[PDB]
Structures are given as structure tokens and as C-alpha cells.
Amino acid sequence: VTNSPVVVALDYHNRDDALAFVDKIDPRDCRLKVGKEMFTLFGPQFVRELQQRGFDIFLDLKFHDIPNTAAHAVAAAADLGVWMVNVHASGGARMMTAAREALVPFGKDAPLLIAVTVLTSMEASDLVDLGMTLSPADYAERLAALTQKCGLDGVVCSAQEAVRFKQVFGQEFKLVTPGIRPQIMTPEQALSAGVDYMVIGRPVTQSVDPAQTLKAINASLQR
Amino acid sequence: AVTNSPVVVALDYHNRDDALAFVDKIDPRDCRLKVGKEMFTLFGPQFVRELQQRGFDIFLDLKFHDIPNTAAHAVAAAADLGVWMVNVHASGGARMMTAAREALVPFGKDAPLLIAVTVLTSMEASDLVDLGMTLSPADYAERLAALTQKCGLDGVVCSAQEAVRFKQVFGQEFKLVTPGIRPQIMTPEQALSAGVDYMVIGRPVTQSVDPAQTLKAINASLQR
Image (cartoon, rainbow over all chains, first blue to last red):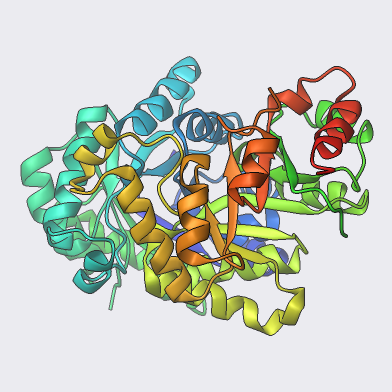
């Protein structure tokens, strides 16, 4: 457990380099994100190492597959004991649902189940290629609602959508947003916009004494 | 680590000890192996190496769908892992598929085959209503198939029901990977005929008693 909304992106290609960083900060201070980089290189095994140091882990693998498989994937993350796991909304309802229903037997131990909507990187251009008429913004929201309708715990979403999404979807719908920078929201702006978990990377990881860096972020968030 | 079979058997076990048992019953010459989200989430690259050290070729079936730089990182990592095939989601878009490819370029012909998922085998018209897609699965997969080819990847995962039309439209060097293959839902026989380049077979083999016979029979049937 921790009170911070901060999730630090571990995007190392060296395992012992990451734990060094990791050892310079504290679980009470924040949670960690393991994504496709570290997980393709290192698998569940390294997640365990982070978990062994008592951290809460966001397994950011955005499962996008057939329902049966997605289901099995998400269960596996829960068996792994991660804190949060995401899926792609664009996999559709049955996938999301089966994802969700898979997590039922872990009861109150089941991780947070979050859906990617429209990737933060995808521009309008990119969406026409796919033959999609709605803006990224409009389409992310449609994807948000589908997710909510499917019973998931929240959505990953841009700062730029954070305000309207909280107003529209409310507060038990967790808002996960990336690209937060102390100095693109600030940790403070993000708090205000209502986002629940704010993913911070280089700002923290590239800080000499990132722990002071951290420390300033949440103190700044105290008010 | 060549075989002449177009067979790729799906390893979808919850327990490793069982997976390797099955593995020990069959031969790299006889088929290829596909590792998906299940076994990978449970057992990591480390388990891929186990299979690869027993001589098998692996299809790392993780269908990377993420931002460009990231998918790029994962695909390169798949390569360094030394797998034979790796896929990505077409729906990640051109910039993503592109970064994937280019990531692989430093690996010369050591590079794994880079395959794109188009419209997942399971998705019905209904499912696409939700997303707001006007085109049928079929039309949409094809749109996605061309984007893949235009992006310069080696082929697409696709349904047997689309295998023939895609071979005709995209040609034969455009690899077609299809699941839902069943000895006796195309058959190994029917699938080849359609022109599908690699046929993914699950339970028929894994849940075959004497699957090594089963495998060798599969390829006997393709003696033709």
C-alpha cells in the first residue's frame, strides 16, 4: 500500500540497473510500471524481483487477443500477483468481459483491470488508415464507455482527456494517465483534473537522487 | 532450425512440466511451436530458450499492440531471443508496423518473420459494431492486410476463410498464417490447397495420444 498516485515507468533493458534505481526509492512512495520492454526481455521472473522488494506493480502489457486467450493472460498476471493489468478496449466487449470474469476467482486479490483506449501516440491520420471516422478523442471516449459498460476498473487516458472523462465517467472509474512531468500535465495539474494514477518516467528515473524527486512530487501533491 | 512442415503447434499449457513432456514426445523436424500470451505470461523468454535449445523454431505469438517505440523494443527483443516468427497488431497502425520492421533490419536475414494480426479470428461483425467499424470483418481484415504489405512486413495472420482470396490479392511471398486447422475449419489438406503458408494446430496434436504419430501423419498427408 501507498498513498501516492505516482507510478514510475521502468523502461530499462538492464535488470540490475533497474533494481539499483528501485533500491534508491521506497514502496511507500510509489508503484512501478513494467511494460513490453522489460517483460519481453525478462518475463514474470523480474516482476517477482520487484515484488520481492515489496513494490506494487502495474503490468502494462495491453493484452489484445481472442477472449479465451486474453482471459488466460489476465488470470496469469493475477497469479503473478501484480497490482494492475491492462487490456485493449479495441479487443471488444467479449474480450474485456472474459478478462473481467477471469479475475473473479481472485476476489479482493484480483488486480485492477484497466483498458487501453486509443494509444496516446495515435494521431487522427493513423486512425483513418484503419478506416475510422471518429476523432481519436471521440473514439477514446466511446472506448472508455464500452469499458465501463464491460465492468472494468478504469481506463488509461491522456491528460488532454482526463477532465472530461472524470466528469463523464465519475470517480470509481480509475483514470490512468501517462506523460506526467513535474516540469503533458504536471503532477499537480493531474491531481486537479482528477486522474488517479499518474505515470512518470525519465523525470524520476533520470533524476540524480530520484528519491528527492519523488519526495517533492507527493509533498507537492499533499495540498 | 528448419523443418519442411507448415505445421505450428500451439503450446497453451498452464504447467511447464507438461508442456516440455509433450515437446519431448515430438520432433523439431515434424513441426514448429507457437508460444502465446498464456505461456509467456507464466514463463517468460526463459521458456522460449528451453524450446529453442531442443532445436525447435518458435512462433512468439504475443501480437504486440503498443506505441511505436515500444513495439519496436519488444520486436527487437523477440529477435535477440532468436525466435523464428513474431507478430504485431495491424490495428496498431502504419507508424507502428513500420517501426517494428525497421527495428528488425539490424538483424539481417537473422531477423524473425514479422507478421501482423489483422482482424482476430474471433471477432464477429457485432464486435466491430462496438468499435464503430462500418466494414465487415472480412473487408476490414483485407484493408489491414494491405496496410501490412504496404508497411513491408512478411505476411499476416488470417482466417482460412480468407486464405485463398489473400493469396490471390497479395501473392505468395505474402506469408499467410492460419489457425483453426484440423486433420478431420479447414483441414491441413484443405489449408495447403488454399495456399496458407503456416497452419496452426492446437488440441488435435497436443491432445493427441501419440501426437508424434499424429504429426508425422499430418505431414504424410501433405506428401502430396
